Amino acid sequence: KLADCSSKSPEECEIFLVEGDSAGGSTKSGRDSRTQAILPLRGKILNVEKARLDRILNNNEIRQMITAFGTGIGGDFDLAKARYHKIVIMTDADVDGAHIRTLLLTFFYRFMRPLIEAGYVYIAQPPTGYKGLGEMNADQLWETTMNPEHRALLQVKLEDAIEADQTFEMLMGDVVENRRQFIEDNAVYNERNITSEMRESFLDYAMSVIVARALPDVRDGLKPVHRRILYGLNEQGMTPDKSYKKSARIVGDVMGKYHPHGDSSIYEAMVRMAQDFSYRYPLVDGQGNFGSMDGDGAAAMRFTEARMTKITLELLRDINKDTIDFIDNYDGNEREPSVLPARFPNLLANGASGIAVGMATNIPPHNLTELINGVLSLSKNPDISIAELMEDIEGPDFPTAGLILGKSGIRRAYETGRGSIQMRSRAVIEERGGGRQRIVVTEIPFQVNKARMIEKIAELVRDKKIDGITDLRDETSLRTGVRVVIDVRKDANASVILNNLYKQTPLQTSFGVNMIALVNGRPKLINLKEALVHYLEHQKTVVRRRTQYNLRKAKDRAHILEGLRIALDHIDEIISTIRESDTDKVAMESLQQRFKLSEKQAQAILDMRLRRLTGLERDKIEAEYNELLNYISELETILADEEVLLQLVRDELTEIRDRFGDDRRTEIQL
Amino acid sequence: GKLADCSSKSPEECEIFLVEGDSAGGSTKSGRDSRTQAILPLRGKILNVEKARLDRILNNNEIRQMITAFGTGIGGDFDLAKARYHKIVIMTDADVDGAHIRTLLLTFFYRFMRPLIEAGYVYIAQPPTGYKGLGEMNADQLWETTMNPEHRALLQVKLEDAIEADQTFEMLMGDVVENRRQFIEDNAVYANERNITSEMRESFLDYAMSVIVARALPDVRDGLKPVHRRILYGLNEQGMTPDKSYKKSARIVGDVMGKYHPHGDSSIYEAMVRMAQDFSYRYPLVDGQGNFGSMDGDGAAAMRFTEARMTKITLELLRDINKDTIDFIDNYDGNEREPSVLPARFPNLLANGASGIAVGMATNIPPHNLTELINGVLSLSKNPDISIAELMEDIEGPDFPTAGLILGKSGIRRAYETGRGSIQMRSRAVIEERGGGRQRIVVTEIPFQVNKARMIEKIAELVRDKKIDGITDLRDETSLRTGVRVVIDVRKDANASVILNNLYKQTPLQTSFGVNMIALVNGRPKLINLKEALVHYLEHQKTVVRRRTQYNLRKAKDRAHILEGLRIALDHIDEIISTIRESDTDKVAMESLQQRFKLSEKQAQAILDMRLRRLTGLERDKIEAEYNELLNYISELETILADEEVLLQLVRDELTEIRDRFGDDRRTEIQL
DNA sequence: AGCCGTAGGGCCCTACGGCT
DNA sequence: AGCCGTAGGGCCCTACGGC
Ligand SMILES: COc1ccc2nccc(CC[C@H]3OC[C@H](NC(=O)c4ccc5c(c4)NC(=O)CS5)CO3)c2c1
Ligand SMILES: [Mn+2]
Ligand SMILES: [Mn+2]
């Protein structure tokens, strides 16, 4: 992968480390070939502070860096064999670039500290506002970043070896809690000291993953990638009524406008939203192969198509009625929603799982009928207890059904945001003839790979670690549903074998509830009541803002209609006024003065087509006006009375419950 | 392997379905009856065993997986009794590439597993059209249409006559191109049980004709293959003009794939990349931002990173496309329209060249200097009977983006007279001193289509292997500032001219361009000479300008007709308004206006659509002026259409303007 | 030879946290 | 252990004709 320089005198030679060949190509084209070598890596490198030594020494990118530098590692590290006197970290100007820099520095510090001490390690400073170096023309890269005469390299300086050791250990080591603490204490919502670099770069990454990747918002239940997909579907009018649209086109659009990351991240998030074994209320309606419970992936995105589900319309409902705040997209050329109106409680309905930095989230899905009944009960009683809420919300309700064992895990999770929930397959024992039996499994636990689970049983039977099983078959089909059959040896006890399978396979699995979501843009562990309270407050705001928007707009339109009504009442004078005017400007002025019109009204009259003078058109103007006056007084009633508003929220939730609410799938056994 | 086997183990009730890959295999696996139906995903095009030797065949992963899965062995050791399935079902995608994969599968079965065919174990599934591949189908649909024994319609493959079948496999799938070419020419039409010979002939012909007429060969008129046409049209439709900002490559590609070009991402993106590369295209058609590859064979950055738009000269390909100059057609699924051909206001086929490997034939057309080409067309426009030697007074020869040298005029002349000929390209190399009484060879230009890094590696190999004497060092000193610079140090006292001549003999420093000018002419492949290529280009331009003139005429007369209606309305506005006001509906008004004022329906409609702001004082004047200018314009257009020589002169003038704006110096030196 | 350029098709390494 | 899901990053097999 090394594209070496022609010179072999270390003192004038430089090596640039880039993320991959997309970046490597702009670099290779821009460089001075004589003195500047280029080593493309392959994205994120091994974190050597967490890895075993042998994994490190067998890692292909680690080996290539060692070979390139020529110095060996650790003990045998020989400075005078360095093939370059500048090693330049040139990752992309994005948060993942920052992460890759923290990773590279960790490796250098732990395995090549003398390289740092001798002042050989540098950080390049490519311009922001590019996704990667492959986005830059070679000449831009050269002039800004690589050319000795204009570039601003940062030389990496080690001051305090003690503070450095503690910094690498804290940020990059296996103990999460110290890293978590560092983030909470530091989170805000020429030479470079290596400790300062590691801390600022690592925090930059940590923060972005926490607030803008891996955790959902409490209000709409979405992570960024999901919000941008759904928003993208909305902007391209890909509603359930219209035909499916090619996935490649959806992804291309989302990536360009909103989500500056790899296609796999976008496509796979969309795919999960279309899987009825993953989403309790699927948000995407997929055409074609969208994967299976056996861990088959979707067909490639060139083959599939998609659109919104009907329930996703309720997530996006009234997004264009000034209900939620828009923000600039990543490059200032587009607007995107900060959050979706989310007219059902999607966070709890669909759940969320997310691996961040310093923390993670794991929120199970719920029955939408129960959830909405929960929100209605809270709406009538702000002081309701978790125990009273559990009269509506019994516990999780997984798309894959199955059993939950007991209530005490659910209770703890709802009270504290954390708890362990034991899940089991739906399995029965039945006769198969000749006095023989079988175990038949028709539902498996949430997030368990069915084919993996079966191979695990096949393995146990082969290693003779389970007695009694004479055959094992997946008889799943579209027509029959999930059906996994385990034949048992004649006169063996099938219940014992079943209990053994629960102990030794994912036929029984735990769900560790860890309910962290973004509240006011900050990560927080929340309980059931707080999730519902944040949801309800969001709904009040959305409906209130929609009411205010509809009021302003209706007033604007009535204002225009009053102008048109005046014009119809005095049409001969209107025509005369315009005919005697030389220009539009003069007409506009005369219309405003003669008939006491606003600029907006005069412009509307000037914009009126002659067809609007026919009988039916005159009547429509008046009908629309009288209808609007009514509408305006309805809107005003709502805004004058907080109880009327709250009731409106309840009636709208009730309508969604009646239309989309469905039966409980997962049985909570006592 | 990825064999997804069924549970039953009685051959006689078991079926195995062969599909193109995992995308298809996932729909198949979700839809199937897992008791009796195994699925084996392949990996796209399989080895053509009629062209490959045994070592290659038996080491091919997909071949091996099929041999293993069927259990019969192959060849002499074939045993029908060990078949693990009594139905082997070919279920490729319902497209031409699917048909190709079917012919490849049958060739394998026929040559290695003939008894399987003879025993009636081989079947062809018939999935429905309108899907890009099986992965586009829901599992229930795939089951009900294709796999369900209660409703499906398998074709059982029958071998009637083994001698005819032998001949068919050899002609269609074998190494002799000419008989395959003869087969296509004899059968092509341009613009249950299943006999295996009939299946092979029909499926292969489908594939071959589709590659010939709709993939691999350029149209003589605009010089474009379908993928490049769809990209450029796509850019135009989304208004990605040179004046607007760069658009992300990923969005262009997804857009083009969705609307026009139902093929892989990499086929589209790489075609776009090439059009943006100034070492590939003599006149680049795409303006790229970011890493778009190098002369060392580095690819472009992944499409997530790059951006693109049209170049200025591409606007000239698309000029007048919205003025009914070219026929639009339905796209592949009937939801869009696309151009059959671009107006192509410069002769793009010869300007940028073309290479393409089809079936039965290929094309290799070198690029040319646009100034020279246009002068050639002009000379032709004045003299239908102009000779090739005369044309060569304007068009000296190819002009490659990479410059360099062409040795002599013999190969050029043969290529322009016949459409075929070998042109010797040579690097630009000089001998120069390097100090200490030593010399070096310096190369600053290389032949078209030569990978610079690879040429350097070939030189290193000659040196390392003692196949060339006198080279002491070898470096690529190329840079953005320097341009291409490859240096070969020569040993003190060695003759550098002799070393250079040896390099020309033994390395890509000198390379042949084999001209083979095949293009689509009236939608069929034709070997054409220079004059024929220019003639068709000139005819296309006459048609474009005539049609544009006709279009403008129609639009002018329509506008004049509306303006006559507006004049009347403004001259009688009070009666107009009163007519409309007493009318209850649109229809009534339209009728009363028409009867009272001798208005057409279009006139009455335009009046009803008139805004009140059009009644201001200077409007009757603006309408009178426009009408007077229009009348003038109309008669100017009528002149053009009544006089062939006027039309042709208008063609000449537009070409000349393009030459003056875009024509550039020759790069490639032709040495005599 | 293997390369030129439109086509068919797919797989594997890395970080991150918490649960087993 | 190693899986879950958003993220960083990339490579190799095939057909086809001509030289
Ligand atoms: C790169 O280095 C390696 C390494 C070896 C590999 N081994 C196996 C498979 C692969 C990649 C194959 C995989 O197939 C699906 C493919 N994309 C599409 O179908 C597609 C279509 C259209 C678009 C699109 C994507 N993306 C957009 O932004 C919108 S337009 C994405 O990549 C390998 C790649
Ligand atoms: Mn990057
Ligand atoms: Mn296919």
Image: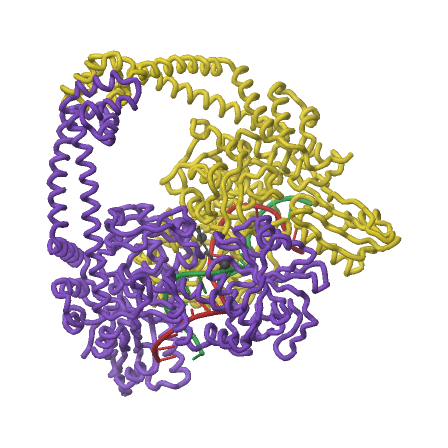
Chain colours: A purple, B yellow, C red, D green
- Frontmost residue, A592 versus B543: A592
Q: Toward which corner of the image does residue B376 lie, by quadrant?
A: top right
In the image, what residue occupies the spot 47% across and 13% down? B639
Q: Toward which corner of the image does residue B390 lie, by quadrant?
A: top right
Looking at the picture, does residue A238 appear above or below residue B325?
below
Residue found farthest to the right: B493
Looking at the picture, does residue B623 appear above or below residue A169?
above
As drawn, is B63 to the left or to the right of A594? Answer: right
Task: Report how many numbered discs are placed on residues in the image.
Answer: 0
As drawn, is A191 to the left or to the right of A562? Answer: right
Looking at the picture, does residue A244 appear above or below residue A66?
above
Looking at the picture, does residue A267 appear above or below residue A70?
above
Q: Quadrant of the C terminus of chain A?
A: bottom left
- Frontmost residue, B234 versus B520: B234
- Frontmost residue, B76 versus B343: B343
Q: Is residue B340 visible?
A: yes
Q: Toward which corner of the image does residue A423 lie, by quadrant?
A: bottom left
As drawn, is B550 to the left or to the right of B314? Answer: left
Q: Position of residue B102 (x, y in %)?
A: 47, 53
Q: Position of residue A143 (x, y in %)?
A: 60, 50
- Frontmost residue, B186 versus B328: B328
Q: Is residue B121 visible?
A: no
Q: Position of residue A293 (x, y in %)?
A: 34, 67
Q: Quadrant of the N terminus of chain A?
A: bottom right
Q: Position of residue B275 (x, y in %)?
A: 55, 42
In the image, what residue occupies the spot 24% across and 29% down? A604
